[PDB]
View (cartoon, each protein chain N blue to C red):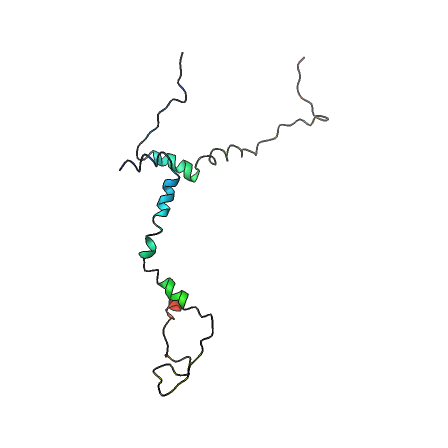
Amino acid sequence: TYKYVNLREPSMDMKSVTDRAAQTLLWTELIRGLGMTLSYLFREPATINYPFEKGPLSP
Amino acid sequence: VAAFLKNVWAKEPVLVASFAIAGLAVILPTLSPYTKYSLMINRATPYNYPVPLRDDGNMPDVPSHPQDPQGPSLEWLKRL
């Protein structure tokens, strides 16, 4: 069937521009999003120590 | 012209904020009385040596004693 993605007209009123004005000017974007999704560093590194450890196979 | 501030602040929100800092910066030094306190201090900073003068008859004011109430009062700042 259908789906129309990335197809949405803007708000264009008094208050909702302040959500798009604080975004560009003071960067509430790009740090709450992209500075937190990188860190996300505390997870365990899933590395195989190849001369000692070995991975799975199949019969 | 009332939406002209609302069809450019939702269109190019960079230089709009510049003109607001172009404003509110020229006007206010002519407004608050905290200025001319800037002038009274910046003149009352002694760089050079205050050389005394010669008496002849008068004496309108200011005898030789420095700790006498003979000159002005800039000592409001220490009380400020």
